[PDB]
Amino acid sequence: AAETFKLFNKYRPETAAEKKERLTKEAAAVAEGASPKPYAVKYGLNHVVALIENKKAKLVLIANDVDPIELVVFLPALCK
Amino acid sequence: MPLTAVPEPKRRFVPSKNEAKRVMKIVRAIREGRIIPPKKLKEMKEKEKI
Amino acid sequence: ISYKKGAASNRTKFVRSLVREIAGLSPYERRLIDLIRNTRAKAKVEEMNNIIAASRRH
Amino acid sequence: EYSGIIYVSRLPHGFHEKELSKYFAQFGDLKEVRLARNKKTGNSRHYGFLEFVNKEDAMIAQESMNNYLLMGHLLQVRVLPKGAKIEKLYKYKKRVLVEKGITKPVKQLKDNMKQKHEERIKKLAKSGIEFKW
Amino acid sequence: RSQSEREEEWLEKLYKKHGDDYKKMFFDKKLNIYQQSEGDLKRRLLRWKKRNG
Amino acid sequence: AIPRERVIKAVNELIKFTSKPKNLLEDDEEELKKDLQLIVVNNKSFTGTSKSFKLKLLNVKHSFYKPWKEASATAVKDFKVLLILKDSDIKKVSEDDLFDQLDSEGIKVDEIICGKDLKTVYKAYEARNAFISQFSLILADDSIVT
Amino acid sequence: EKFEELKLSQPTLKAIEKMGFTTMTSVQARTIPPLLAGRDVLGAAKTGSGKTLAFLIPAIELLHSLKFKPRNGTGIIVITPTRELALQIFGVARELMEFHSQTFGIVIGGANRRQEAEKLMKGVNMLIATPGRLLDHLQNTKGFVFKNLKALIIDEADRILEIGFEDEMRQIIKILPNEDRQSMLFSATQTTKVEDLARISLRPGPLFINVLEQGYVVCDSDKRFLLLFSFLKRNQKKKIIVFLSSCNSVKYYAELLNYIDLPVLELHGKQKQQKRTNTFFEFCNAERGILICTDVAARGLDIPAVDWIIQFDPPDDPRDYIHRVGRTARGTKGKGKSLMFLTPNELGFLRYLKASKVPLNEYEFPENKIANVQSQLEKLIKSNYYLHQTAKDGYRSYLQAYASHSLKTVYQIDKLDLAKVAKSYGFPVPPKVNITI
């Protein structure tokens, strides 16, 4: 678990403030006068479930304390 | 092999379009003086706090 | 004709069978399985027989 | 049954006899710790053996480190069957070269080179190549 | 319905680098950032040429 | 030094010997059967008692990598060139600059890498081997080579 | 024997001129005039002898004269034995109706069931189809109007009965109308079953028209294309003709090889007729280069003298492939060496080579000399949308042509590892393709 969160913490998505700052810098550059695809951890239940059944996820972390536990009971079986 | 044969959308291969529209909106706001650019803001915080 | 009677999608059958395998068996279905090993009713018994056959080998 | 000897494999760089002993002495008293190295230059071969005084300490040392993700490596620790002694694992060091020789006199050493040249010239004649001088 | 400044600059660059070769403008990774078909490129470039000359 | 006639006859004899007389692609033995090598032996070691990883550059009259790249068109492995540069000098030069000042002579720099790329993206042994083994000429910055 | 000689419509002449055909060959010179008279033909012309236009032009002319509409249903039904040949016939027919107002459609195995059903719903005036799916669409789809059938054409009846569609053909004959229908049959050869089918589908008394070892390489399904690329790159100076199973795979391979700086030419049934003629004429005089084409598209064409003929994909007609290794050597006076890529699962094909008594030679390839461009190909497929789509289409077509092969004892799809097949197309994970496995 400690080694898994060292890899997953290097692909943390940008926060609202950082994304806004990055977009405003580009906007200010344009207002005066070719990038690679980003990388981040995928989240959201529906998004990850859609990724799993399309065979795109390389590794899926499932929380063990979802209060309506039926939200994630099918997930280990779907992943296997 | 996957469950469905839905084709891959073209928006997954090219840069973001929502961000392009948002950047152009910020550009339009900057040109109207509603948003002070970060360089000008950095200039204004080195001139008063004395 | 309408879509409502078209067919069953691959994903739909996949989801139904996965939920069947995960949820378990209701008590009367356990009784039916025990009885078998030792129109609604026909479908239910055919489902139980399919479950038995899939549990055996595949 | 089982022995008190555990074989450890897929060791990272810089995890040698002293490091292995220091880490595995916390699971019990040790009796022998040896690491495989290259003979020509002292360099870890990334596996080794070590024996516990208590046989039941080796089982605990094996159950907790058999799939340890360390330095990008999956340590492979396993207990050996009954008997299965560990031996012949020397702690080699880097072998420096010694420049010694020229025992033969310069006259004989210089005369042998001529006959080597002549024999070399004659050698290629039987290999479908014509070469003069 | 007139084009924008940035679109006109992009079409400027495309025309100045390739001319009327739509197949190369389609496969160019630096100017066709949003990979667009030959038909769309031809239509927009024709509009640009008609407006300019 | 060496009379020209002896070297000429040696090369002619090697050419004759190398071609005396199922498989889709030539194997290692057949691929490099015609490679030419000059063996030079002195008294005692060449570089003393210290290992030298530097290459001695001997001047040649005729280009050595031009026929290589020309004859690499009909080979499974292309002739690629790698240029390793310093961290601070990786942004001062682009592929366009080397294209402008090198295509007029026939030279193509296939890849330009930094020293930071050798410790992040090609750190793993397999990836490093796969990347490095595809180049036939590696030119390193004078400061970074050591 | 010119096209302008026969009295035809204006759109027909426009289309014929556009494709570039001026001097009709003998097969289409001694059959089209009798066909415009309305009689029945039991031909014997070989496949690719120009008979396609010979049985097409009367159909378009009849539809134009009767002035069909989409709500009239189908008027012409063409029956073909193989999935890839029906695609070629449909591609040819798309160009004879560029200016006409009729409607054309294709019904083949492995395609979308509901899409074909809806195309039938809208009303298709000329249907080109395989026997297997015709029965399903006739007996199952409601709203497929076919009572207005005016003509029926059977292509390669010998192939149809060889594959085993004779029961399907009998049921189809029992379903389709018979009175207003003037029918047509073509077969290169004729056995008892051929006239058995001809009698129950044609009017009585119809006019009839009369017209060096082989090598193989055992390769893995995840390395077939990479080894092929290595071989082609190593042998660029020679002349090589590469045969593929489908048109989509031909176009994907040609586009990929041109993208990686390896000049090749392409022929497939989804191209213009003028484009095909231009490329094939170019290939016959360039004394260098590689041409990639489908098996069926290179049947009628007279193959020139080339240094290598590679059969990358399983042959559509193995019975013809066994004979062609000697036929093309009888024709071409040069040493045209043949090669055939076989995967370990389909290695039983050699039996047919041994039983038919042809010399057999095996080729080896070192494992470490392969091109090692898999990473580049996979990076390119994930980035270029157009190349991604073309690769997926080629994968689809390859699987669809592999599933419906006549030699089920050799080319069975159940023993094909789809992950390794998609690996050769640049895909880490196989795309989903709706095939019964």
Image (cartoon, coloured by chain):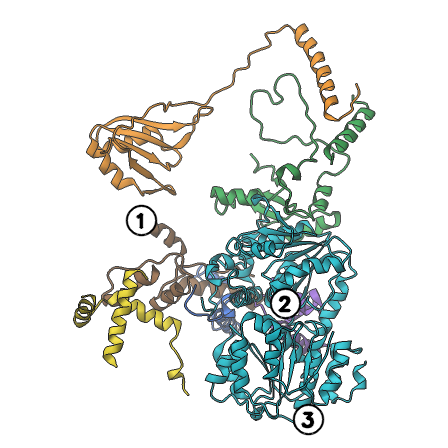
Q: Secondary structure at mark 3?
A: helix
Rendered yellow, the chain in question is: C
Q: Residues within 10 Å of mark 3 (few under 14, many from 20)?
A: few
What x and y, as percent, mark residue D37? 41, 27
In the figure, what tint was chain D given?
orange
Callout 2 touching callout 1 (CB < 8 Å)? no
Mark 2, chain letter? Answer: E
> Which mark is on residue E26?
2
Mark 3, chain letter? Answer: G
Distance in Å between CA atoms under marks 3 and 2: 44 Å
Amino acid type assigned to the residue bearing label 1 in the image = Ala
> Which mark is on residue G65?
3
In the figure, what tint was chain E given?
purple
From the image, tell me which residue sits under label 1. Answer: A2
The C terminus of chain E - image quarter: bottom right
Amino acid type assigned to the residue bearing label 2 in the image = Phe
Q: Give the residue drawn at x 77%, y 32%.
A: F16
Q: Secondary structure at mark 2?
A: helix
In the figure, what tint was chain G given?
cyan
Specify whether F24 is left or right of G210. Answer: left
What x and y, as percent, mark residue G126? 61, 85
- 3 or 1: mark nearer the eye: 3
Specify whether G428 is left or right of D88. Answer: right
The N terminus of chain E - image quarter: bottom right
Front residue of this view, candidates G64 and C9: G64
In the figure, what tint was chain B given?
blue
Rendered green, the chain in question is: F
